[PDB]
Length: 393
Ligand code: HEM
Ligand SMILES: COc1ccc(C(=O)O)cc1
Image: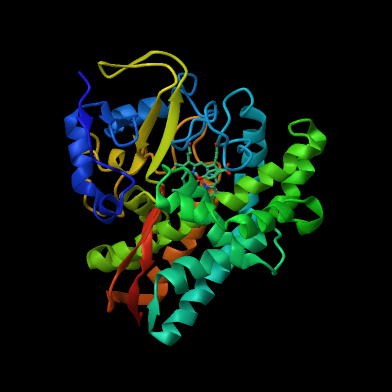
């Protein structure tokens, strides 16, 4: 009943061009079996959306990577929120939703917008820049570590740790093992900055510690919650912004539209999050024998969700290979869906929007003048290098 496919969704051949293999996964059926790693796969929007919204059947406490925590020791102490299920997940989730609240976005927006404007001015002075290192990477590193109250020393560990977290969700390929080996320095730095005395007052980290008084979390849970904001929220926004810049380059007509109405910047970034989907895959583990789309999945089985393919499903999207800044992107699963939907989606959209706002008002054209290099990760899709030339507006 269930087709078995030999496609390796975590291979370098897959990462370089996943879209043909993704149609093959969608068209093979609503549930595929992937012999390479002995997991179930779902690639259509309908089934990816259904598993994300059935947390009781498709749990997260047994890991959201390939590894089954009930079977193997996790490479690090499990996340208090991403790798938890209700009710254990509920009160840590409420804390992060209040720390990263709409009320919190008002205190940082003008600081995040001003730094996005100054960065674009800075790169327009240099003309030919690397949109990844000098823009996609440079900007969020100039606002987010400060917004969390991180000290200046050691910030070079942040990106290496971020890419390690997402490589570790993957299978035991050499991408994951090279990242886990010699990961001790980044782990040591991140763990120490989780302690309250190292978090500047007013930042995200100190705010999370301030929530121990409420009875929502205890003091010993606070550092691990801080760890989530140092593991997630950097590498996804970098790839997300680098994709938007890449899209504006390959679709110059969309850049001219954003230039004519810069209030499209927030949706221009949202459509870029659907179009590229920086987080490409996440896992769930079955707690039951479940009937999924006419296909029976047993207990304790890993189910791989293809979020990027679900965002390009022609059964759900009109012309999904097209970048449309005016597309009604509502319902995409780049940020997830349900009880685990990104808790930091407001920070990402804010970072993305103010950058695309700055570009819309200062740049006339964005032209690629150099070899584009892909960045390879077990979980993230994004560019390694995007040589661009910016023409001032
Ligand atoms: C382009 C930007 C981003 C993308 C594409 C993205 C993607 C995702 C996705 C798909 C999930 C769901 C995981 C699951 O259901 O298993 C998630 C959860 C999460 N994200 Fe994001 N994210 C982004 C930005 C951020 C930011 C800015 C932060 C923090 C400041 C953040 C922190 C988190 C956390 C803590 C969770 C776990 C929430 C939970 O388990 O309830 N992410 N993210
Ligand atoms: C979606 O990416 C992540 C990665 C790590 C965590 C976490 O540390 O809880 C959450 C989300």
